[PDB]
Image (cartoon, coloured by chain):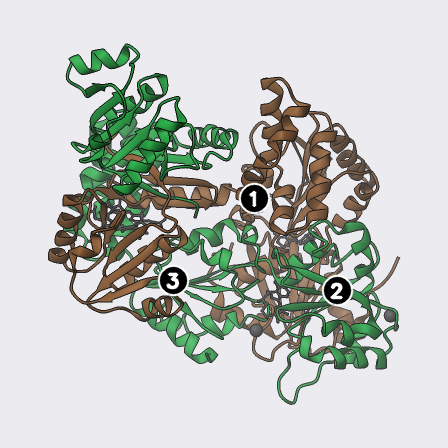
Chain colours: A green, B brown
Amino acid sequence: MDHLPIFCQLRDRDCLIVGGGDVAERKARLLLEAGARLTVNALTFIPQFTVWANEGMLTLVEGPFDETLLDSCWLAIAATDDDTVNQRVSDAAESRRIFCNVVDAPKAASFIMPSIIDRSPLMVAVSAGGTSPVLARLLREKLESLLPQHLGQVARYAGQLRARVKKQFATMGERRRFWEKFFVNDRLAQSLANADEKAVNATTERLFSEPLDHRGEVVLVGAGPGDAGLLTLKGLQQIQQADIVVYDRLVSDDIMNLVRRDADRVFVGKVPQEEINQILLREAQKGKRVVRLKGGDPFIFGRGGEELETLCHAGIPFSVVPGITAASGCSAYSGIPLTHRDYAQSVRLVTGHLKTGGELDWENLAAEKQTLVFYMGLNQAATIQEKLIAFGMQADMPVALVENGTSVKQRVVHGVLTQLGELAQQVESPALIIVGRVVALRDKLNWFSNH
Amino acid sequence: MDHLPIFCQLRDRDCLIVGGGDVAERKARLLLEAGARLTVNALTFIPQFTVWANEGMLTLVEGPFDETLLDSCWLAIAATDDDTVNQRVSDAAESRRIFCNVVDAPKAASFIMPSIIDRSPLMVAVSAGGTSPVLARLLREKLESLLPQHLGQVARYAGQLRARVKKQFATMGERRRFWEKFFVNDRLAQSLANADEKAVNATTERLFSEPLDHRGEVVLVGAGPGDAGLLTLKGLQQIQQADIVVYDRLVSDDIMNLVRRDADRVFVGKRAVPQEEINQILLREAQKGKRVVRLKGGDPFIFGRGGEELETLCHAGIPFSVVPGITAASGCSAYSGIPLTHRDYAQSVRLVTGGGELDWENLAAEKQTLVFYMGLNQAATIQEKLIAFGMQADMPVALVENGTSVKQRVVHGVLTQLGELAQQVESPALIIVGRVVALRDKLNWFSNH
Ligand SMILES: C[C@@]1(CC(=O)O)c2cc3[nH]c(cc4nc(cc5[nH]c(cc(n2)[C@H]1CCC(=O)O)[C@@](C)(CC(=O)O)[C@@H]5CCC(=O)O)C(CC(=O)O)=C4CCC(=O)O)c(CCC(=O)O)c3CC(=O)O
Ligand SMILES: Nc1ncnc2c1ncn2[C@@H]1O[C@H](CSCC[C@H](N)C(=O)O)[C@@H](O)[C@H]1O
Ligand SMILES: Nc1ncnc2c1ncn2[C@@H]1O[C@H](CSCC[C@H](N)C(=O)O)[C@@H](O)[C@H]1O
Ligand SMILES: [Cl-]
Ligand SMILES: [Cl-]
């Protein structure tokens, strides 16, 4: 984070503006609306300032900068056209540990003032750190269109109900569930906007009267292969409302940042699968809303079935949000479609890491007109090469390995089947092996990166 | 207003957190991300704090709150479970004019913490003034889905490019039109994030070379199998920026409802259309300078002919990209309670299409999950051939019609019933064959129709 956004309570707190022109006037108006106890220190003032001072709304100090005016201050704003003066102000503020904005130099000093979308008491602040005023304006335009004008009345009414919600629901889990219903009842929002107090009260009474599900919940969510843009809308929804998220190392850091910030997080793996099952079950038996966040898709070599197979008998509600499997993401981001024209009748998603005595069906895998995708197969790439050749696959069949597919770190190496063992030495886990004529299309379809 | 939002520069500035449990750890994570020179003071610390301390990321002071720890501090956060301690911290900070937050307390705080959407240098913060923390979270979720992951990359790159923008643009009206195209170029942002200097330089020169009104590109977007919640975040972001959306019947109405109202729409599906005509539409519209989204059911590269649509473009000089989607196999699997793999049931999953002809001995072999796309008409033949090439007659089979939608229909039985079960469903439907079908009785959670 370049900056930390905070929302300050300035009511009755001393603040100082140095400067007295149009810039100072805009900042002073903002600080006055926030209730600051404002002093303005400038050599000259535009007329808006003199009337403010006579009607008692702020104090004017007409003259050069007096750094002792910072002594009682919580915030300072340097708003002159003299960079020498502005720097004296910022230096004096920094020595007193007073957050200071230099209006014409956002990279100097110690805070910047964001653009504000006002749905009071709801506020949304936007800034690009001065690097890009256009982008901030384009975002502000877009945010103003997304936020209904009546949102403020919903937030206002919620604040008025917080005491009643605290009294009537004994646990935070119940309170949270009430609010999640409250904030999406469109009728309630309309009635507030119409000041229809009878209608507001009717829907409110009913919301308070509803029995709340105290049962837990286990949702398996497919994180996808790494690019946080490949999480589904519903997957984002589920992790944003989870009490606890049980996640593995194949879930990318970018995706974990999208988890509800107050959710508890439990890491598994690098842990035996039976202990994962117990965690999910036990945490849901406590009434908690559990998300098992899994790399790729939960039902393709993810053991997702094992994690749910006890829950029905145990009376635990569950659901599954599918994800982009490694095969799909790596295909798209390497320029290798899994199917194309008559290249492949079928796609085979194969595990390269099989049970101790198990052996893959090589005669079956080596058949023509298919795209083979090996998961967890790096260690066996030499055997895969030898077996596919022995069961009739052409030696010049193209192969590709995709390492960290869809991430900014993705790497792709490629060649023909007789190089598979050598090529696999050039990558590490997590990596996918693609075998089939579609690999040759990468020269025409690669769009994501050359690395 | 009742609170003034400011964006604080905390890099190497002394900040104090009082508390050492889960609540304090969340605040410490936030202040560390902002670069704060952080001290944490608590009667005891959970293990995350000692880990951080050993890696030199912060300083720990084990013991009761000592208000002299505030003497050089710019921000304070009271994050204990003891109201008396938190009030001592808040009073000590206020007497020093140090903005102070008390977590899970509205007043006695001189600042409150908003929900944060980080695209640094770009940042968005949402606050309801203490009235509605859940509303702030819900708005964060909405904004996180809408702001592309790498927007901060272009925001930073804008700097080293303003000398060139004004040497080529003298009017104020044109400069904004350039930036408007620049900041929505998600390809450039990803290439910057990829550290792909070759791609960055190529995309940059095109931004200056082409006319202002030209924004030609094609994005293949996987709509998923129907449920609008199964669109990816990037898929949503792309359809929100499209000049024109080209779609067909297997893109659900729910997904099309997310299409930016205003976008020109071209329907290429079944009514009462050769692929070449579709390829040319994408080509022609891209060359007219339009940002074109080709929305496809499921995933574009799994029986979607997405490759055919793109090879038209690579040698026409038209930039393109692909957003994968949830394929029908994955969506139907999740929503029917039939995992495609499970324990040792299946060593492989086969996604298969219903000149040429299928290899039946291959398809009949054990330890597979078969998923037939577009096979509804051949379902009687699939039954006969799988039986005749040795698949067990008692093998479970299922058909999923309109998978993931509110009208999803799942019928199931055994291989000898496949032809008759297929009469009970309509396209689009998936046929699933394999031992995993038997898990539906334990795992079906979605309503059947
Ligand atoms: C005043 C404020 C404190 C301050 O910062 O000064 C406040 C106060 C309280 N929160 C409480 C509980 C919850 N807090 C959250 C979530 C968030 N709380 C946040 C900030 C704020 N919380 C401040 C201003 C809020 C505003 O602007 O409207 C967020 C946005 C920012 C952050 O903290 O990081 C963060 C989401 C971050 C993200 O996910 O993006 C949830 C929901 C959830 O967990 O999903 C719940 C449960 C549901 C509910 O109770 O509503 C309680 C009752 C405790 C109890 O029951 O005893 C109080 C006390 C009270 O005021 O009643
Ligand atoms: N980003 C990535 N790039 C390449 N391969 C990946 C990958 N993420 C997962 N994999 C593959 O997936 C294997 C783990 S098995 C779990 C796969 C996951 N359920 C899915 O649907 O994709 C790894 O060994 C690797 O072969
Ligand atoms: N919602 C759905 N439910 C069941 N099958 C579906 C489906 N959507 C698409 N299909 C299957 O896909 C076939 C069209 S081929 C298109 C496949 C798409 N690219 C994907 O990845 O899913 C249909 O005949 C049907 O078998
Ligand atoms: Cl599995
Ligand atoms: Cl071959």
Quarter occupied by the C terminus of chain A:
bottom right
Disc 1 residue type (three-letter)? Gln
The correct choice, above or below, for A263 with respect to A78 in the image is below
Disc 3 residue type (three-letter)? Met
Percent x, y for residue A359?
A: 70, 85
- Residue named by callout 3: B57
Q: Which mark identifies residue A413?
A: 2
Q: Is residue B345 left or right of residue A52?
A: right
Disc 2 residue type (three-letter)? Val
Residue B242 at least partly seen: yes
User: How many residues crowd mark 1 within 10 Å: few (<14), some (14–19), many (20+)?
Assistant: many
Question: What subunit carries mark 3?
Answer: B
Q: Is residue B42 left or right of residue A345?
A: left
User: Looking at this view, is B434 or A294 the one in front?
Assistant: A294
User: Looking at this view, is A135 or B42 the one in front?
Assistant: B42
Q: Residue at x 69, y 33 (%)?
A: B207
Instruction: Name the secondary structure under disc 3.
Output: loop
- Residue named by callout 1: B153
Measured in 3D between alpha carbons, the distance from the residue under mark 2 to the one under mark 1, in whole angstroms, is 27 Å
User: How many residues crowd mark 3 within 10 Å: few (<14), some (14–19), many (20+)?
Assistant: some
**Quadrant of picture, ligand 2:** bottom right
User: Looking at this view, is A84 or A145 the one in front?
Assistant: A84
Q: Residue at x 35, y 25 (%)?
A: A79
Measured in 3D between alpha carbons, the distance from the residue under mark 2 to the one under mark 3, in whole angstroms, is 37 Å
Q: Which mark identifies residue A326?
A: none
